[PDB]
Length: 269
Image 1 (cartoon, rainbow, N blue to C red):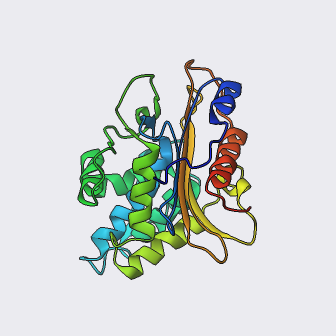
Image 2 (image 1 turned 60 degrees about the vertical axis):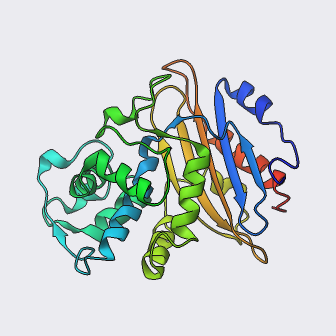
């Protein structure tokens, strides 16, 4: 069996952080995995937005005009942390541009407009069910979806299910080939993850990712596809939480967990 062939000190890492860390990493060549708290639930925070963009792309396979459709919105749509959509309030943006902003800047107004167009939290959850993910659940609209309350299963998934779904969408057959490459390209252009999984990945390897930062309960995360040169790609997810509302998240802890995961797979980095 190919899970955790090499032990890594995840317990000491989460103890120093003062919380819990969940990790699942897959070598798509051999099938070997690294797994630590991988089936526990952790808050998604903004990381749901990557799967939202994939759901939009899936719909575009049946609606050739969807991605270029212009969307206008009012000032009431501009909630905190809407860095791209606030620059186009007076003009509108296309569905594709809103999707890119949601993925690459974690733009909240853009994500809310797209979620409404998909049928809300239940519509995104239905898309995840359609690719075989039985763990993911989105339950609320922003901003309370980021409340990260200990023990609350709303707006959560597991590191394992996040990785399995990411693999299906970026490397597998869940999206048609043009849409698959567009999803990969949006993730590759993310701007918010330079201190997380990317900090553990050599600069000469390709990588795409989506981050999340709830702002409470030490809760933050990142998931990524990584293409080391000369071998098959790696898919991984790192999620954190902590017991007290004012516990701080740590980007360094996410980068360190990613390093341990790559070491556990025997990937020289």
